Image: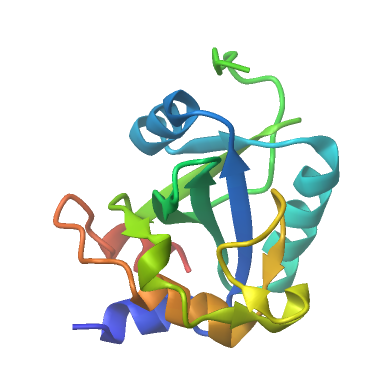
Length: 155
């Protein structure tokens, strides 16, 4: 069912994350980490203190799909062991869905905070309004590799 997911997403903030390659998403999916440029890192750190959940929705550029979504479990932090991304601080994230959603399945959703353009359109770090982000996350298929239990306790 969707009760657990809807609880996680209640009063959440949502950000589009645009990656230039699949490799960094694969790295991030396995390790539960993300890093972004300074302007977005600041925005995400502010959101983490302001909302019960901050959700990152990933799309690899030119892929025609979203590749999943994840919830920030921390603000960014420096000084950790370097992540050899295939080119700011590192955010720890808990993935909620690592399955793909093609843009054809989100064609009816428009983001009011991006001039009511389809939610698939946006720059890295584009914030997605609450209801559009919630409905977008609800479109993803269930991910049997994921247990929401950890997230629900962290909240």
